[PDB]
Length: 167
Ligand SMILES: O[C@@H]1[C@@H](O)[C@H](O[C@@H]2CO[C@@H](O[C@@H]3CO[C@@H](O[C@@H]4CO[C@@H](O[C@@H]5CO[C@@H](O)[C@H](O)[C@H]5O)[C@H](O)[C@H]4O)[C@H](O)[C@H]3O)[C@H](O)[C@H]2O)OC[C@H]1O
Ligand SMILES: [Ca+2]
Ligand SMILES: [Ca+2]
Image 1 (spheres, rainbow, N blue to C red):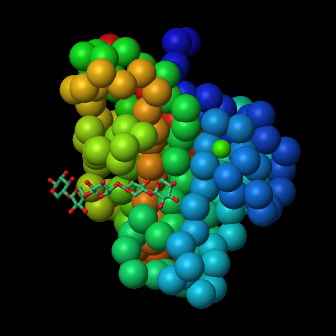
Image 2 (image 1 turned 45 degrees about the vertical axis):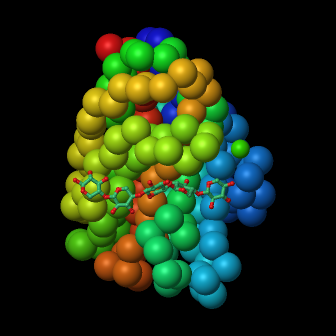
Image 3 (image 1 turned 90 degrees about the vertical axis):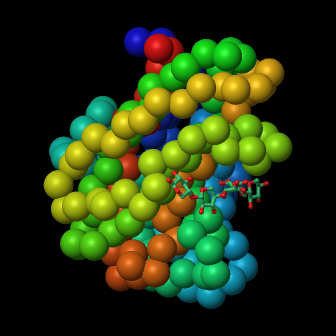
């Protein structure tokens, strides 16, 4: 496969809680805003249930901030070509009913090219997919996943298998 993103399945990363948010996971930047007073737990988990490889990323939300992007996992770098249309696919599930996640892609200037907005995450693995086009002249973009929805308090959201593919 030819994918734009790096370590889309977390297989590069040792199992355990991630405390180095910026650099602890190859190909990703994790972020927690200061309005989140009970910070989430990001953990790379080795599990027989992983849809891809042996590992998944678990995001335990024990509270939230002011905006859903106050808890986020962003794939970076994402290597693309101007004008090209990509398919984004990822797998996600949650520990408990009722989770909400937005899957987004944008540039380093924070302009958003597209998203899946307030996706309904269930307790079973499901794929979430959309297309976007690089509408400007960027070659290195990013893919922010937003987890800080109030409905996720008391839940863990599991993601795996991010693939951003030409089309
Ligand atoms: O440390 C820094 C981080 O804080 C930083 O985080 C990034 C901040 O910028 C974020 O991008 C903004 C996200 O919000 C976008 O506006 C959205 C767009 O979507 C709107 O919802 C639409 C509703 O209707 C639907 O049909 C449609 O599908 C939806 O899109 C929603 O209402 C708006 O809030 C802004 O345009 C973005 O700029 C980015 O995600 C974060 O990663 O990152 C850098 C780091 O240094
Ligand atoms: Ca995996
Ligand atoms: Ca990083």
